[PDB]
Image (cartoon, rainbow, N blue to C red):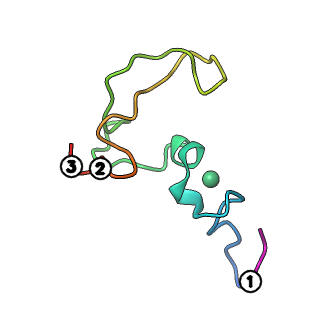
Amino acid sequence: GSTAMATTMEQEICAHSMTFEECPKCSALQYRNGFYLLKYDEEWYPEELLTDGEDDVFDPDLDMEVVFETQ
Ligand SMILES: [Zn+2]
């Protein structure tokens, strides 16, 4: 958090000691669109959200920290 930044961008790294676009909730914002279909992959209907019980637990199928090309 504000280590050696000042140039312009100050979100290149989320407060999670890592890239912002490399986080979940970060990608949950809907910054992806490989297939511009409002989605990419999934197989788990909406429900018990991320502790938000908002009703939407989109299964991160074919889209993880490795399952993004393999299986
Ligand atoms: Zn983040």
Name which residue lies at 36% across and 36% down.
Answer: 39
Spatial CA distance of label 2 from label 1 is: 31 Å
From the top left corner, tell me how far across and down residue 26 is, in percent. 58, 49
The CB of the residue at mark 1 lies under 8 Å from ligand 1 = no
Instruction: Say if 46 sits above or below 7 in the image.
Output: above
Name which residue lies at 53% across and 41% down.
Answer: 28
Spatial CA distance of label 3 from label 1 is: 36 Å
Say which residue label 3 marks: 70
Instruction: Say if 46 sits above or below 4 in the image.
Output: above
Q: Which residues are magenta?
A: 1-5
SS for dot 1: loop
Q: Main secondary structure of the magenta part?
A: loop
6 left or right of 19?
right
The CB of the residue at mark 3 lies under 8 Å from ligand 1 = no
- How many C-alpha atoms fall within 10 Å of the one at disc 3: few (<14), some, or many (≥20)? few
Residue 4 highlighted magenta (yes or no): yes
- How many C-alpha atoms fall within 10 Å of the one at disc 2: few (<14), some, or many (≥20)? few
Mark sitting on residue 56: none
Say which residue label 2 marks: 68
Say which residue label 1 marks: 4
Name which residue lies at 51% across and 20% down.
Answer: 56
Q: Are marks 3 and 1 in contact (CB under 8 Å)?
A: no
